[PDB]
Image (cartoon, rainbow over all chains, first blue to last red; front, top):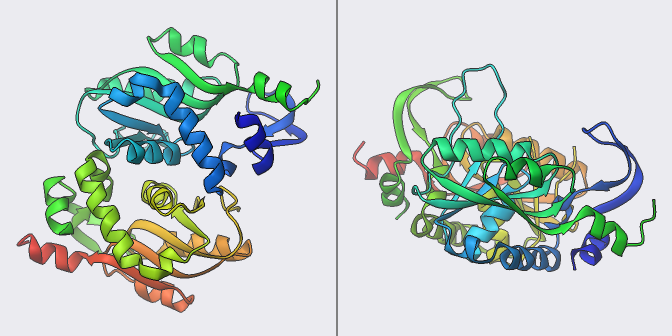
Length: 177
Length: 167
């Protein structure tokens, strides 16, 4: 049950915010706050391994969506004694060529991010992976905002799996709205 | 044992580079390539833990330098059952408990990225006296960090690596 751990670490904060989607929100989500407490990130890692299931367990490598999903991907890779790789969003118009940092061996991988929003950040990582000789059909996140990410990824042959949805977390915490 | 691991993963590249120090060099070290091979990063982690010694073991948290030193810091934190935090060279992402922490990065050149992280850590109440990296290029990082009261420890210097590889 992430909800409890999230509240404890302030990973779910009450307030008055504006999101990049343009929507006004009474909640700010920050999964990074779970990293500063072994008790908290361990619970998160165990849940990620659980939902990742066999896809993650048999993956030739774990790929993180830099930055956000990088610590999680690195920790999962170490727990599974598997190769790690990651893709970062590069500044545009500078002549930069994308790459899968870490250069894990070609094969089937699972991409990992902390929070799924629109799904575009994950989609970009998938395109880089597929263009560089990797195969990927699963994206794993801790929290899915439930705002179109799954549908967008489904349209490009990728199944999004999450430990929890924002809606479920807010309900459990008796957030109101 | 790090030199052989680097060679096997093609972490040492040749070319015409302009280092962050402003000096030109024909060598670039990409430590990220070790992450794509479990046998390689496990060795690197073992060496980091060895060189980190008690300073790393007694820390209240391991702090990584986004993005380069982030996987290493995250893996060290997990292996040490310690909190993780990181700075994007402001707040310390992760909000680890206040106390004496150790900053970790993959390669130290000018030491600027590490210095920035230390500045942010201290502004937020943390203390730091040690910085840990896999490779120190000897491009001023040790001096810069010493100036701000931080001792830089490295698994190896680029000089040692190049000599071992016969470069």
